[PDB]
Amino acid sequence: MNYARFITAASAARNPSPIRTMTDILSRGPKSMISLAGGLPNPNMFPFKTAVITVENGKTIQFGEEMMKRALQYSPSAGIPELLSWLKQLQIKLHNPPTIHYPPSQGQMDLCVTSGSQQGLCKVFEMIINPGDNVLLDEPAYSGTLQSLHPLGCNIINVASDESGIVPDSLRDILSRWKPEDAKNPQKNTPKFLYTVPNGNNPTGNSLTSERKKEIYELARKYDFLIIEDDPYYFLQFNSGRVPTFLSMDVDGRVIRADSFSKIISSGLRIGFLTGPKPLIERVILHIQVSTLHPSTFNQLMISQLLHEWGEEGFMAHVDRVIDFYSNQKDAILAAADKWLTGLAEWHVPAAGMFLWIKVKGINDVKELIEEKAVKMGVLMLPGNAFYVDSSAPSPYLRASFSSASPEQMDVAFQVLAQLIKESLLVP
Amino acid sequence: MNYARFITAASAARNPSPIRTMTDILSRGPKSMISLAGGLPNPNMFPFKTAVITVENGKTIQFGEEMMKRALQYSPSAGIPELLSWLKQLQIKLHNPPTIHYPPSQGQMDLCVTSGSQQGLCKVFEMIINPGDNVLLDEPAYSGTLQSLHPLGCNIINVASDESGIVPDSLRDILSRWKPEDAKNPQKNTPKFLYTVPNGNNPTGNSLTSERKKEIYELARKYDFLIIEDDPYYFLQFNSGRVPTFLSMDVDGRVIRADSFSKIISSGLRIGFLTGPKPLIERVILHIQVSTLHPSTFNQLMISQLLHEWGEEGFMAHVDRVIDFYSNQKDAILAAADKWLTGLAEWHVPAAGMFLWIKVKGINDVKELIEEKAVKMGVLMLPGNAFYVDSSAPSPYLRASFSSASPEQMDVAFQVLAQLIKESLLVP
Ligand SMILES: Cc1ncc(COP(=O)(O)O)c(CNc2cc3cn(-c4ccccc4)nc3n(O)c2=O)c1O
Ligand SMILES: Cc1ncc(COP(=O)(O)O)c(CNc2cc3cn(-c4ccccc4)nc3n(O)c2=O)c1O
């Protein structure tokens, strides 16, 4: 593939740090080397000495004197080597990407640890988007993505979707305005990429099927666009097993995948990872180098130590317990919606994640009913407006999270909503 | 001050996330509220339970069950409130900025925690720079800043400098190409900003005097440009007292200051902070919101707990012990250079920081000596090329860090350097 056409002039202009050549020559010189090269501060000046972190339950992560000095010091831009190698093997085990052994220039599978998956996505959007470029996505979409794309000056083209996510026939119809050969044409503006959240879309809770992913991938090949697979709910699917990902079917090296530890390990530690073709991942790493430099070494070492002790089996057993908890939370929110909202609202059973997307029946805009009337009654939900490119347009939808509230709290919240629907209906 | 004229259309287009709006109406409603509006994962699913971190020396930082759940959860984009308030008070005590009580629109002093000071600088450059803009700086300059500015398409104008940093007469001569009234002219390209490292410039080690800062500030007012004060060695000055900063003389609200904890507390934790006018700090926070979201909550809580227990006095006492250690390292590197390099190289005594900037006599380019010959002999130093806009031009300079090597290691390293210089001197 020609990666240069999916890279801005600014992104292509990025050069590596002078410390890259120094690290490459460090592995080509003697063993007992003296370095006065790096701008590394003295680790003995740091006030934190050792650390003990207890793990669920009875287990213990310990940072001795030397490990603590490493944790408090600068580390590689793409992430610590032990976390990268464990994650690489996880990706091979979970997705077996076709690109593992491709030459670097042909999109060889590459990884980098990011400060949450949001950082990876942002660098990816900034690497690709020139003002006026065309991008594809299905609305309602994650507000963070829309807020990230809005300043970039791109035209966002909405792809139709249903309970099984993106409708491939709608994507087929949209793309028919171009001819496949337009992707090679400098005077044509064929879409740079398709962005999607394939499992438990934020805010709908809907997931793509394997069949639909195969059809979407074939259209991405035909019109030569990238697939940005933002999958933070991959490890939060309600069904047993896992639907094959876009990365698993990536024969062309056209998929950039974002994974997150936010919903399973910790959101506050800011650790996620990007998997994709080496020429694109390299552009992202060069941008990280001049911004955050690297993700927290301390946080990476905590997660790396946990993952190595658990192994892939202990990791998957932990995700299984997390899924079990969210599955019960999902049943409790569905039971509250059944009790109070039957006849008043419409909702689908979410396939993954932590949200219930509710459509209020005889109301055009839910914003004032929620942002004002519901708050006064002691209940807060998110109005749907925030999940569309045109956020000023009226929305009868609301997003309700089932991650934290108790069944009794959900019952209170839904009873209130039901009376406010009956209130906004009897108004002349 | 007209802040919109300094920023890009993309930066001005940034909008806040909806989670800020929901928090604004949270305090505006009852106390025992049920909120299904948020997107926070359930914290009880996170595998880390408690933490104990030992501090220098005999002291301990503890994260109980509830504090650990906070540390592992999402937190505000600008930083945790207790770290922000402690940092705000430190800035007032150290710099007493003239803008503390200005209205928000007039550049009221504002702060935000960043994932290292490099993130703050990068967001600041991205917020300001349109291709073709003129920017001022003194070369040799920090490689990270040059590598960051290079993709932005700006014209970098070199300001002459000496052992006391930027020469105000050179800045005066450069600016004379414009008339002060051109700064109000949209069709003129007057400089957007002056960037400088006022204490222990990376790589020279040179520091600006108070008198030079006052003259530079007056030129910044006359031609209406911003001052980007990148000061990571502010807490690493070898001279007695601290030279007043650009922020301390900032009557106009034209200074953006970057501070770093990398050289004093931890480089690996990725915690720094930006201080500047509220309209500009807000644009940076809005960009952080779509990228890293926030700095690690865990890392901020560790630093915040340490700073609150130390107090500002304990913090300043720690910086004194750090300066004392680097002052001794500086004497050891100067003694090693005197012994091995006299007649072979030239160097100035650094005023602050951790680097010795060495000019090799009789050689035009030190790159092959440093990147190949020295590495093979087991010694690493940085060639000077990386500190200039034109990195391909030959450089007789090298940067040697005195932060980590022992006096015995410096002696070995410089004996090797002397040997290689001698070898080069004999080749005709
Ligand atoms: C003027 C100025 N402005 C801002 C900052 C940024 O500081 P933050 O940490 O607060 O973001 C600095 C920090 N400088 C350096 C930081 C460096 C880090 N590595 C390194 C070495 C090995 C592995 C990974 C990284 N090597 C470094 N070298 O060589 C440096 O010079 C600065 O000097
Ligand atoms: C599809 C998709 N893609 C990527 C990501 C990013 O994940 P990372 O953490 O890996 O960067 C998500 C995460 N989503 C959300 C994250 C949220 C964080 N806060 C919050 C709440 C209070 C204080 C501070 C922040 N509120 C949030 N809300 O509302 C969310 O929906 C995602 O859903």
Image (cartoon, coloured by chain):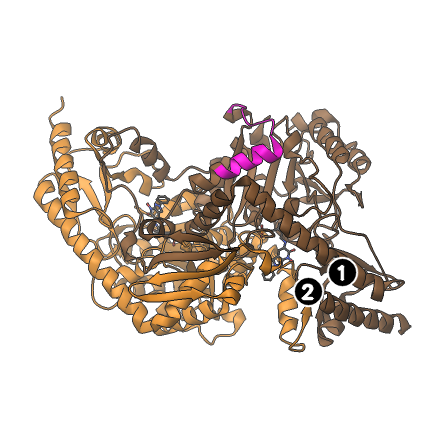
Chain colours: A orange, B brown
Q: Is B248 on the left or on the right of A375, as rendered?
A: right
User: Farthest top residue?
Assistant: A428
User: Mark 2 vs mark 1: same chain?
Assistant: yes
Question: Does the magenta-highlighted stretch encompass residue B32?
Answer: no
Find residue B77 and report its horizontal and vertical position in percent: 43, 43
Which of the pair A307/B151 is nearer the observer? A307
The one of B393 and B285 positioned closer to us in this rendering:
B285
Q: CA distance from mark 2 to mark 1?
A: 9 Å
Q: Is residue B182 above or below residue B393?
A: above
User: In the figure, is residue B184 to the left or right of B26?
Assistant: right
Q: Nearer the viewer, residue B146 or A263?
A: A263
Give the x, y percent position of residue A423: 13, 28
Q: Which mark is residue B405?
A: 2
Residue B333 marker: 1
Residue interval drawn in magenta:
B86-103
Which chain contains the residue that carries disc 1? B
Image marks 2 and 1: residues in contact by CB distance under 8 Å: yes
**Mark 2 residue element:** loop
Residue A217 locus on image (x, y percent): 35, 64
Amino acid type, residue under disc 2 in the picture: Ala
The residue lying at 31 percent from left, 48 percent from top is B40
First in sequence: mark 2 or mark 1?
Answer: 1
Q: Nearer the viewer, residue A66 or B366?
A: A66
Mark 1 is surrounded, within 10 Å at the Cα level, by few (under 14), some (14 to 19) or many (20 or more) other residues, namely: many
SS assignment at label 1: helix
Q: Is residue B408 left or right of residue A193?
A: right
**Local crowd at mark 2 within 10 Å, few (<14), some, or many (≥20)?**
some
Q: Amino acid at mark 1?
A: Ile
What number is the disc on residue A403?
A: none
Chain for disc number 2 = B
